[PDB]
Image 1 (cartoon, each protein chain N blue to C red):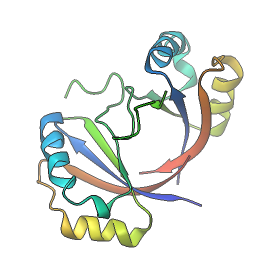
Image 2: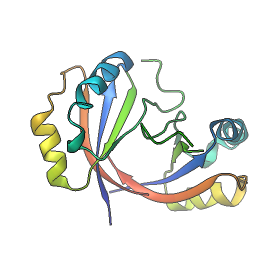
Image 3: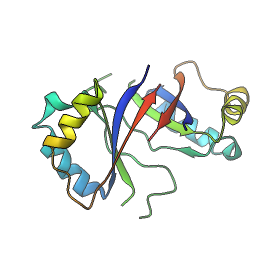
Image 4: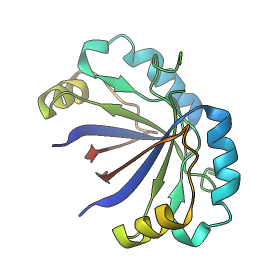
Length: 81
Length: 81
């Protein structure tokens, strides 16, 4: 009863270039969000993209195959919304 | 090991006015996001705000106290990111 997710946090321009990059690998995620942040907190590098996946296996394939620059923090988790 | 959440989906201008409204009730949520959407899907009314809470009790207080217009879909769930 959950959706496996990845969040990408960092600078909004890097994240934008990263999106160019992963639109080449569209079979490896189900959805990706516009770029957002928590209101009040992005005075930083605290911009975020969320991706959703069909399974944890598809998520592993994304992270195996899709190289994420080191200036971006990658967290994995789940959602049930 | 989870964060109770609310997502608000609907038109971005309504959501913006709603944010004016709930900044008056800031003790009743921990964080609220900028307005976002799933890329490709917002050709609609498919814009979104996420709020996070300290507990499910604080979430109930938010939804008890903070009236949400009917043009906005309110879903509740959890995240672990």
